[PDB]
Every structure is written in structure tokens, then in C-alpha cells.
Length: 160
DNA sequence: GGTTTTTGTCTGGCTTCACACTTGATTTGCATCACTGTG
DNA sequence: CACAGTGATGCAAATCAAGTGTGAAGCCAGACAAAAACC
Image 1 (cartoon, rainbow, N blue to C red):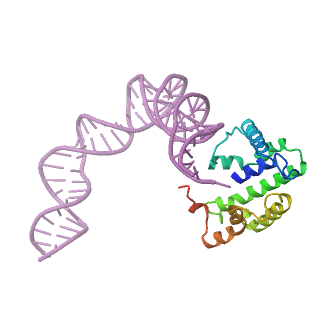
Image 2: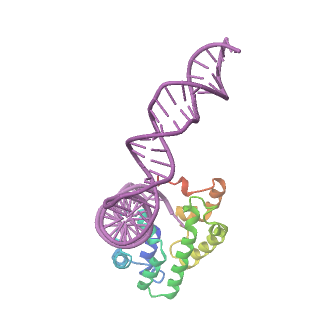
Image 3: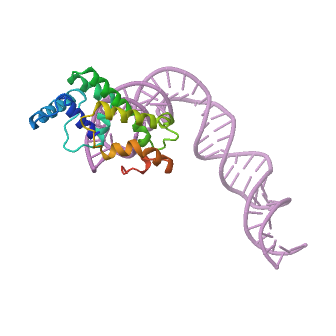
């Protein structure tokens, strides 16, 4: 979700049309996103991101509120489908027992991963060519093997 | 079988607690509300 | 889909206070009378 914050922060300025930008433009995008977040979702800017911020910003209303700052309807649809895919994927690895708490999300995880992969490769070409983050690689590749090997993922987390 | 312990009873009579109703008049319990905090 | 708080508020539910005449239970008397675990 911190990387999604960065994605919104970069896309609010329409980087896909302007490949080059200055740190002043980056700070402008920072300020606009932070203001609109505090105005609509009642959040605050935080220096290093935490779990409560992650859960709040991984909501459909996050994109439903940030689309007002970007003009492109194609970008609106792309962000909406990206958020939908991530929210479908989250219960698989956050469930305390995915075999008896989200079988519908477990049965189509591979198809959702393929759709997310193709969307990242095509519609967000400006960031994910030759560089993909560790956590997206893990989430898109190794989750079904982990759930088949162990039985659950969220039970073995470090929140305790 | 003996021996000791462990429970059972006997009826008249005593105290002690629960209840039978009803109409309010409190007092107790538990869910709601949007949030933090360790990352 | 982290989970245990954080306190004020509000409504459902439990307890009760008033009245007297009952039932139901526990126990007192001293004595007689069956089960049961070791020889």
C-alpha cells in the first residue's frame, strides 16, 4: 500500500504523458494528494507508513476519491480495476484460514494474478519495465505454493 | 461370620426460607461509535 | 482479513419493594435397623 501511495503520487501528475519532471513537480503532487486525502478520507500525512494507513488506503473509496484529481477516464478505469484486483487478492494471504474463509478468492487467485500482471505490464509501462518490487513478485508468484505447503499465511505473521 | 463405619427410618413439634399474586421503580448488562498503537 | 482497548450513551433485562397467609425444607428429640469394606 505504500507503493500504491507512490503510484497515486506519480499518476496524479500524468507522468505517462510527461516522462520528465522536477522535484518541485513531485512535491506539488505530494501536496495535492495529501490535501485531498485529509479532506475526503480523514487521513493524515505520515512519514513512514503503518498498517492502519495501509488498510484505510486499500479501499475502493480511495480510488473513488483520487480519481477526481486525474482527468483521464482511461486512467480512472485502470486504477479502479487495479484496486479491485488487489482487494480480491488480499484475503487470500490475510485470512487466518483461507481454506474455510475465502474459497471463492482462493479458486481464482492465479487468474487474478495473470490479470494484474498484464495490467501492470501494459497500462503502467512507465514504472514496471525491468524493475518490479519484491512484494509484488512474492504476491504474484509464491502465495499459492505457500498456502499449499503450510495451510495458512496470516496465522504465521508478525503482528503478534 | 465379626467389627466398625455409613447411612436409613420413626412422628410430633419447632424454626427458617420460598412463594402466590400484582404495579411500577429502580439497578445491571452489553452493544455502538469512530479511533489509537506496535509495525 | 490484528486485536485489545477508549469512555459516554442508550435500551433490554434482572432485581425488588409493598401486603399476609400459605407450602416446602431443615432439624430436634432418643432409639431401632439395614448396606459395606477389612479381617
